[PDB]
Image 1 (cartoon, helix red, strand yellow):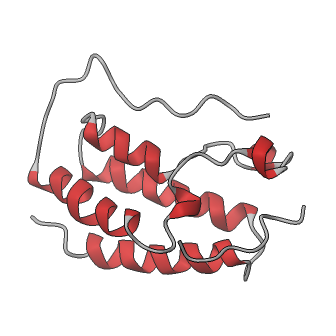
Image 2: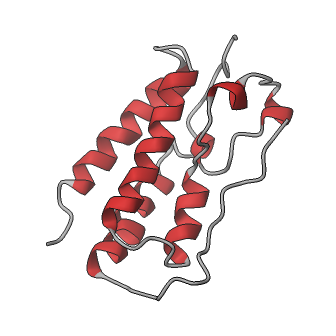
Image 3: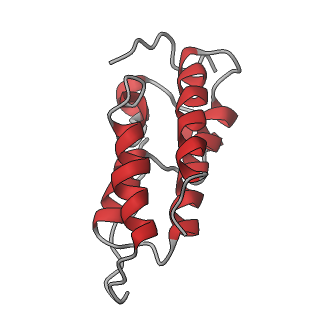
Length: 10
Length: 124
């Protein structure tokens, strides 16, 4: 699977 | 595709408040909850919205910080160990599902470091 991708701080 | 979320109350359980459980809610959970990396972990993984058809095939024991917060608020845990177990499960799920080095894994690593710093100071 390709996972969840980009994650930026919130 | 999504399971029902974990239960957050235990009706037959006596209420037992302790300083360690107050510390887990108001120091440990609060510190992670307010952190800039908290948001991917504040609610159950929504595999429908995120298009992750294998997530709940790989992750058999889902856990998230929203569930832990509600469990602490409802006095679900008998002791600190049970709560620490749920935090560890949350981190474990992230590290088993996501490829090492992915953004969410770097976020989990930082949150886990902070978690362990606070757990090391759990009051006696």
